[PDB]
Structure formats: structure tokens, C-alpha cells
Length: 119
DNA sequence: TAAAA
Image 1 (cartoon, helix red, strand yellow):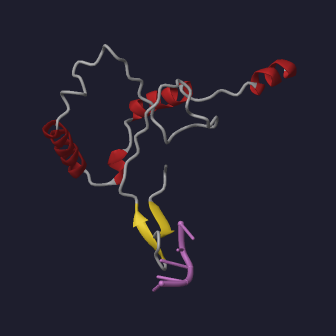
Image 2: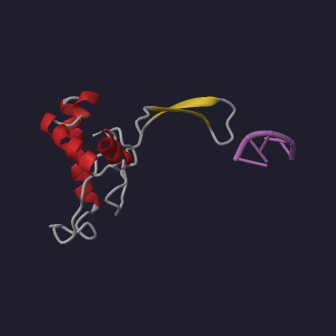
């Protein structure tokens, strides 16, 4: 997920070439516990989506014009500061992100019994 | 075409 380049050989190529990462990943799920890592999940930012609270339906209200406008807005914001530092969350946003990632992360059970036994 | 798949 956190790889900036992909150094690999083409399907039938002769030598290994270098491709900068030109894609963004978005994942979809209905499980409430998808983060297997127990020592922090800073890569993945879970957004909980609620039906019947969607003001606009993504089936009939997202049209190429609307997504083009969204990407033009993103282009403006990125061109305000064209560096990777501008892509990080705000301090309070990152603070909430820690709690959200922990809440959606798998919990180890052995820790509880170890604590009880040591107590 | 063989490879590489």
C-alpha cells in the first residue's frame, strides 16, 4: 500500500523497469473489523458509510460533470501546495484517525488473560 | 519462432 515505485519486469519484457506509483487505492467492505494489524494501522483510513443518510444518490447524481468538478477542485487544492506534505491529515483529523483506526482494528485476546494472570 | 506464461 505504501510503495512509491514498482520495480518489476514486464509480462514478456527483457529487463526490469521502474514504474512510479500512479494509482490511488480505495477499498470497500461490510465487515466492521478488517484491519488485521494490531500494532497500528496508519495506512488505512476507514470511513463508515450509512445508508438512508445519503443526501444525493451515487447512482443518479454522480455524473462525469460532477466528478470532473470534484477533480478540478482537488487540482486547485493540490496546486496551492504541490508537495506530499499537503497530502497529510490535519492534527485533529489525524488524532481522530488514530481512534477510528484503533476502533476498526482487530483486538488481541491473549493480552487480557496475560494481564489478569500477572495481576 | 522460441521463450515465457
